Amino acid sequence: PQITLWKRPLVTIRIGGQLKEALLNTGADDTVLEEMNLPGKWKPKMIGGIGGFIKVRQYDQIPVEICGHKAIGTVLVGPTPVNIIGRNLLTQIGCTLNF
Amino acid sequence: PQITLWKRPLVTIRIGGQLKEALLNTGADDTVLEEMNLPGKWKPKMIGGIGGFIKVRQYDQIPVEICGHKAIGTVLVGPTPVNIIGRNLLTQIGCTLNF
Amino acid sequence: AETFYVDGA
């Protein structure tokens, strides 16, 4: 599909069985999801943004479906105000920027 | 052009007669550039992101050339970790997300 | 507004 940028590019994604709304973010290297109790082993990580850094939990090889498009990879979980789909997953669904 | 996301989507922009490198960011409502001098009056503003909020200077109706395409809009200047072109200007150059 | 730049470092 083709998504215009008049409003925030939010789409539905499926992870850990739950359906959530997430922002297609070309400005994020990684995918960061709001705090949620995901099972599995994880590693600590710090990610930076505007303002500073926050601590998050890193989970590897987590299946994520974006608009019916299947992907799998690293997902970071922490105190973010919005669910963010970064480039690590965007490249997997053949997403590009065009103008 | 069509831009893939295996690497950060950086492009050259020209503003105030200067050339700079900026990140095409669909996850940002506004455009925020690193501290620099710009003609005109500016109003203090605050914007937020992953690691909290920061104080920025707001300049209105500023011409910005992005990859050869012209845009004229609001440009925020402050202590951002990187130059960011947000949706306010991305929509002006007809940018979209596709997959 | 909200600027969600994320540095994977």
Image (cartoon, coloured by chain):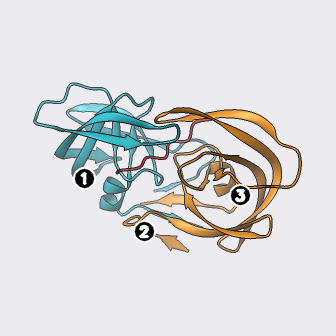
Chain colours: A cyan, B orange, C red
Q: Are marks 2 and 1 on the same chain?
A: no
Q: State which mark lies toward you, 2 or 1.
A: 2
Q: Kindly identify which residue carries mark 3.
A: B92
As shown in the figure, which amino acid type bears the numbered disc 1?
Ala
CA distance for labels 3 and 1: 31 Å
The kind of secondary structure element at disc 1 is strand
Is residue A84 positioned above or below A72 on the image?
A: above
Circles 2 and 1, Cβ within 8 Å, touching? The answer is: no
Residue A34's x, y, as percent? Answer: 35, 30
Q: Residues within 10 Å of mark 1 (few under 14, many from 20)?
A: some
- The chain letter under disc 1 is A
Give the labeled residue for mark 1. Answer: A71
Please tell me which of labels 3 and 2 falls first in the chain: 2
Q: Nearer the viewer, residue C7 or B11?
A: C7
Q: Are marks 3 and 1 in contact (CB under 8 Å)?
A: no
SS of the residue under disc 3? loop
